[PDB]
Amino acid sequence: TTFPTLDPELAAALTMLPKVDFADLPNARATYDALIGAMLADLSFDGVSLRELSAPGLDGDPEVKIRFVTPDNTAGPVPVLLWIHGGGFAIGTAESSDPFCVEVARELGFAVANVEYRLAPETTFPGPVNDCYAALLYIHAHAEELGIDPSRIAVGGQSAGGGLAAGTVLKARDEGVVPVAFQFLEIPELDDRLETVSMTNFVDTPLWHRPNAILSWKYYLGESYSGPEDPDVSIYAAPSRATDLTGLPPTYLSTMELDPLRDEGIEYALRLLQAGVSVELHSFPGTFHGSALVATAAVSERGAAEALTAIRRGLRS
Image 1 (cartoon, rainbow, N blue to C red):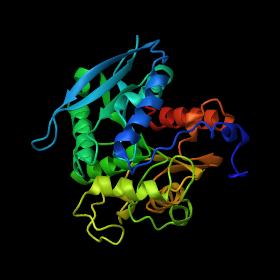
Image 2: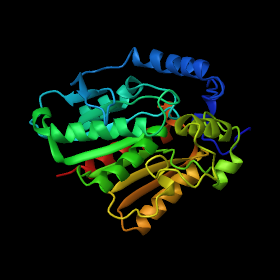
Image 3: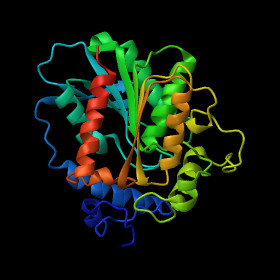
């Protein structure tokens, strides 16, 4: 009865849920890595292979590792999804997204380039988005050797990874080097200004909330960042701040009901549509930020199936 609009299935799974409090980043990383780590242990890699790639960093930056998942016994060249994990820019690892990357490769027969970007605050913007764009540059320049069709590259990610995907897609369009066929943004973190209704009213929602949002953007953008009224923030950092969304790729964007990120998601999708972009927007009822973790709930299964359908169609030949 704390959150009566919650799906009952999602309802259960809310006592267990540990708090991820950004205020203590060492413990937040620790609690996170523990919920990720036990789940990976049983993950099946049936029908796929995983190898590590090294993409040269942008500028003087270090190499960016990529967990490259490919389907067994396929013709190739196949489409590829560049995938970017979440964690509020400051927590998480690429291996945390192995379950989804395996699912895409096994069910769709697509390659998946899962990017190990550097975390904030140790590496502030622009480093993390530069790592993702470096990875995109690499997979595009080496597609033949990698067995990828360069005309069918998707860029996607979840939460902070969704913001990094959107920022990478803006940068890709602006630089004009790599064509991106499809953009997949799951519960994306897009706007540092924290001024939408969901971001002002959702202060203690499950997993993500206004207290964590303030910390996330501060960690990411660093000490030259004066907060939401700062007028000097890159659109690659905060894609919501972009004014020209034309010429961006066909996009899928999902949001959750009780997520503080919900409104910035819906608003970016609407502005993409108004700019002439083909978009699928889906705000799921009775959900919360991260409730896809409850994979057996029917609404989670529905969203998982739809993600596959969306990516399959987005990269169709």
